[PDB]
Image 1 (cartoon, rainbow over the protein chains, first blue to last red):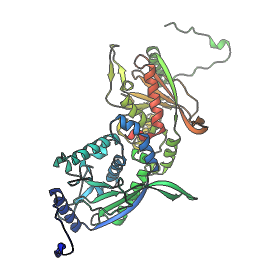
Image 2: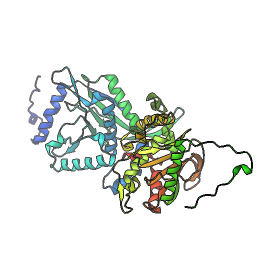
Image 3: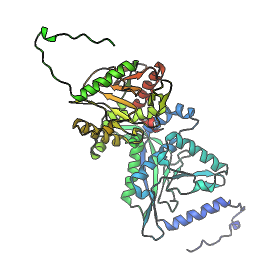
Length: 243
Length: 243
């Protein structure tokens, strides 16, 4: 692939060289390898989380009694695990022969933690089997170990899917890059009060922006549209996970 | 125990003798054995099922697609199974030595089916592990087999708890009899719209009457009051089963 021509940046003013941590360099390589290997499409959707939010906030007592903080992330992890089982092509990878998908029968999900040294994506194993306060505890632990460089490379392996949440900082939507060999990554941005037509008038609903990027070789437009539609449906009423 | 004196009923008018099925006679014996063995207390509670009802009715599409009818019974079975795990003394039996409780580490629940021949209480095994549409399917099957005399005595065994629902016929509450060696039975009656004080005014909420009878040798008043309070809490918001 043609390289970018070097420029003498100091011809234009003062420059300074800072170096990249080995973590950034690793990260840089993996993103570039994914970019050139995966033809990316991003499907955008918004989910009504007004009732989910009310639930979160009411269970503040129980979560503190348990010592966990219950954010949107365990609710997101539980719903994507239910969906990764319903729509199995999202829980799979392209076999190196280019002619088979390896469908995984397990659901481990990674989530992006941005640390000073670079991006880490710890993996919670068997998300489909853990409860909201279990995933809350564990997500929190893995993030603290990630920040404190105590995350062992074992916990960075064998994910089937990645959630990347930037809702705590800002933004309306973004187009994340698939962590190949996974086949999809869910970006989540900031929730806002939005007018939503109730058939007769506009009601304020709290809306969560979702950005699903996927590997278009494995997932086609209709399948990905159906995945963010079911996810918006499960987040609007998380009780559907019970049936 | 002193017998009831025989009366010549025909001195007062015409009488007719109909016989009891063997099922009624079995049933008659077991109830009398429980009655004389278990000092019974009934704890009454009401649960707000307005939102549960809305959920039931909205999932009518999914349940029909699955071929199951989703009544209140699978929702009741799922919540009592979660609770039978939280409050383990309800999931136990008095050991024959009179000095130990056998705590069961499994949750199988029976439910009363009134058939022409008599009462049958089929048992769904491992209710804690099945989903609302799974319990819906299975409850329906077991009831049809019960009515059609095809219920094998295997499926009438090893229950930990019994739900007896008469909400489809009527009534405000009743005092059910514990099926010893179990230690409790939940009676459920008809839901009604009821005014419920919202701090400022009376709001109509749909209220489900619950009647928990228990074996007072094993369960004391505070524990049973806490059990129907948690059950009313879980039925008012079934999402708490997710955490």
